[PDB]
């Protein structure tokens, strides 16, 4: 037993990380089959970033202007094109370590692992949520751009995120692997702000179930509530409203624990109204919202890959 | 910027995980060169675990009684011996994925990554501290035994932990890779308890430095203190006493931030005396002690492997 924020094993992703250099700018790329995916802002100077016309900047770039280095070996780039906010560099060698993979656009509230890289070399790995306002709160230093986020289902890696920007507020923004940004963000150094940060209610509930399963139950109270009643309360605390789908999704946890979803909602309500009074739940003094219901099930039954 | 509890990339360790089965018991082993390391309690029934004589139980086991399976391939076991609380199974094939490695006995307060495995397959990876009372608080389900903890320095993996026991209290105990337990624990299902859980003061300080570097400085106050003064306070809050060595170790962070170690100690003192008043530091409502000073430096400058 015991419950941790756990990333997926990163080996399959490690073998896909390369270094992409164009002009003075170096960042990370993802080498799958004979294509290297990286942020298009690889082509920009720091001055360019204030107001780039990527189409114009791209005109002055040829295949030979993109140095792609996989460990100590130079890849020959035989073609390139822009797809939304990513570059696809066609290279002449298929990555021999290409895993079974998908590209997936994840929903707000869903979680994934980030393999933070610099100069195409991995630094570390950690679990993240795509927040309701479409930012993530990661750890991304200079050079980290092109680092990816992913899930694994057995042998298949689903890539969902590529890092592109740190906003003035210190939060992080990026795209799916087709290069469309999560949220309204653009690949320009301007004032952009994320909206109100809201908590992923369904995730908090899952985490409370994980707690109970693990012996933390001091927070279980004698009340129940209704979806509408609970949601009134959720609104005030900037919690995402809870829907019947969310309830359905929590069913297996409800069943395992014998605690009806709405009874757990009532426990959550008291916690929002009265706080934790200096206590903890699974070694946290606040309500953790970076575990999905599936994450909880996955850990609590020990699914492997 | 931004600051996360980050594990080391796990690829190098993944390629060393196997499944060890003896009788009805299956767990994980670490395959390095031509040796598989696993917990000796692989040889025990659940009844045996109440009071095992490992020497006697071992007498009835031959090489052929240990099924070692690396992915889908059976390894031939050509020798076996007991070293403290681990078995070393000599197999006839060197692991072709053996990385540069060391075995190291870590000190209390030091951190490492755990690759949680079941049936020799990885589940996930997360960062841990060896606590002052020699337990870790992990996530280890049935079958997880033999999962390892490690650090990486560039290409060299330093293995420091193998999981063996969950205590009645839900905390976890294990050995170094020579099979000596951290702390007083034994590989028997009896009442054993860890002592008083104390906080790793030097780590809390490092984390406060990480905070400041990242823009969280609301907790900086106008006071300083002395080692002795601070320690009086530390005693009361069950914080490990701070020594001159710890101060020395924090020097680079002191220098980068321009905040003297003893001034940061005074900030910490007020936090212990007055709590956080419902505020957070790097998105935590309590004092995080699972980052070493080196961890902080490592992340804040983006060291790769």
Image (tube, coloured by chain):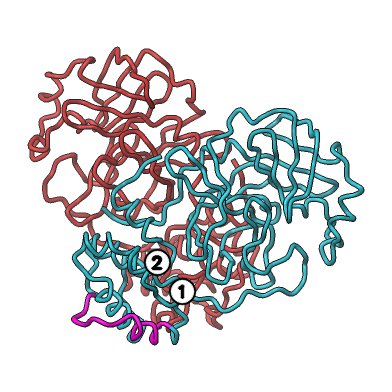
Chain colours: A red, B cyan
Give the secondary structure at mark 1.
loop
Q: Position of residue A288 (x, y in %)?
A: 43, 65
Asked if residue A58 can be seen in this view, the reply is yes
Position of the N terminus of chain A, as image quadrant, is: bottom right
Would you identify the image quadrant in which residue B209 lies? bottom left
Q: Sort mark 2 into few (<14), some (14-19) or many (20+) by Cα contacts within 10 Å.
A: many
Q: Position of residue A277 (x, y in %)?
A: 43, 84
- The extreme right residue here reads B60
For residue B136, above or below residue B13: below
User: Who's the residue at 69% across and 57% down the image?
Assistant: B164
Q: Position of residue A176 (x, y in %)?
A: 34, 37
Q: Is residue B6 left or right of residue A27?
A: right
The answer to whether marks 2 and 1 mark residues whose Cβ atoms lie closer than 8 Å is yes
Q: Which residue in the structure is indicated by mark 2? A: B203
Q: Sort mark 1 into few (<14), some (14-19) or many (20+) by Cα contacts within 10 Å.
A: many
Please give the range of residues in magenta. B220-234
Label for residue A286? none
Q: Please tell me whether residue B294 belongs to the stretch shown in magenta.
A: no
Letter of the chain that mark 2 sits on in the rendering: B
Q: Please tell me whether residue B227 belongs to the stretch shown in magenta.
A: yes
User: Who's the residue at 42% across and 40% down the image?
Assistant: B154
Q: Is residue A300 left or right of residue A160?
A: right
User: Who's the residue at 48% across and 71% down the image?
Assistant: A265
């Amino acid at each position: 037993s015991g419950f941790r924020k756990m990333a997926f094993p990163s080996g399959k992703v490690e073998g896909c990380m390369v270094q992409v250099t164009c002009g003075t700018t170096t960042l990370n790329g993802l080498w799958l089959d004979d294509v290297v995916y990286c942020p298009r802002h690889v082509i920009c100077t720091s001055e360019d970033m204030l107001n780039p016309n990527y189409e114009d900047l791209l005109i002055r770039k040829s295949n030979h202007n993109f140095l792609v280095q996989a460990g100590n070996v130079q890849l020959r780039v035989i073609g390139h094109s822009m797809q939304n906010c990513v570059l696809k560099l066609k290279v002449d060698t298929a990555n021999p370590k290409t895993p079974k993979y998908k590209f997936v656009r994840i929903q707000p509230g869903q979680t994934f692992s980030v393999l933070a890289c610099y100069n195409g070399s991995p630094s570390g790995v950690y679990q993240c949520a795509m927040r309701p306002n479409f930012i993530i709160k990661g750890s991304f230093l200079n050079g980290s751009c092109g680092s990816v986020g992913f899930n694994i289902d057995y042998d298949c890696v689903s890539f969902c995120y590529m890092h592109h920007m740190e906003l003035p507020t210190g939060v992080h923004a990026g795209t799916d692997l087709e290069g469309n940004f999560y949220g309204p963000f653009v690949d320009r150094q301007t004032a952009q702000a994320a909206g109100t940060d809201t908590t992923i209610t369904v995730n908090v509930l899952a985490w409370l179930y994980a707690a109970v399963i693990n012996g933390d139950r001091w927070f279980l109270n004698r009340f129940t509530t209704t979806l509408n009643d609970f949601n009134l309360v959720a609104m005030k605390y900037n919690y995402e409203p809870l829907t019947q789908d969310h309830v359905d999704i929590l069913g297996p946890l409800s069943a395992q624990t014998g605690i009806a979803v709405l009874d757990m909602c009532a426990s959550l309500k008291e916690l929002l109204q009265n706080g934790m009074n200096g206590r903890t739940i699974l070694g946290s003094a606040l309500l953790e919202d970076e575990f999905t219901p599936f994450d909880v099930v996955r850990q609590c039954s020990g699914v492997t890959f």
